[PDB]
Length: 288
Ligand SMILES: [Mg+2]
Ligand SMILES: [Mg+2]
Ligand SMILES: [Mg+2]
Image (cartoon, rainbow, N blue to C red):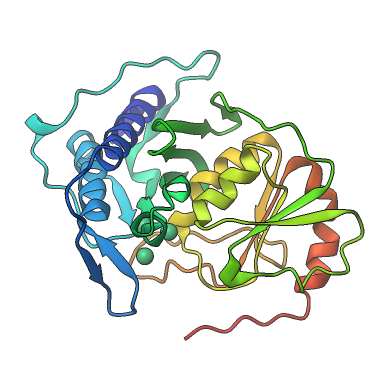
């Protein structure tokens, strides 16, 4: 029924490292399955997910864990790396209840970025809730030396920050080019185009960007939670396009889409929330 936070964080970090390493070291020909809604999936996505699931469930067989892809655990204990024994500075090592935990996984965010050699946009995302409340976020960028960024509540791992721009930077994909939606923005600003939803949140975390405005029902729980915990630990904001907290259902039977969109603000961009809320105020998002 219970475990320590340090144990738990070590298991998750071990899983993410191993998955990231699997992705970055992979030279065989990729085979692209197409889901029944056109979206891509490769054996690299699924193998990454199995690694993550197997490592975690081998320690915590009861644990609630939700992943983008349709695979679970299975990889036998003796092919899995041993668990790291890291300590975490002044962070307090809590006893926690396994059944209060829910884990949300994207084994490979930017599957299309991957298949198009946009390797810089590929992330592994693992986020955790505890009693419904976001608690841990772990992000890896396999093609950026398997760099891992993570946060546990208000504590945050080492992170390189680009010198602040001074112009406010909006970041979006070309396909969701919101530049016309924000022409009335009060202060000087720029639009940077970046594929990958994980990548776009990381851009804010590394101060390459300030605002990620996603007034669309394209994001899922696993796309946001990991980066959310980190950005929030930095003092940034993640919410609906109407300013409310993102929802994280407890089961994959329920829809994992963020149906009221996504909005992320850098610490300094928090003052622009009212502006963004008045922009979103007349939008009714519809799904199909
Ligand atoms: Mg997909
Ligand atoms: Mg994915
Ligand atoms: Mg994704």
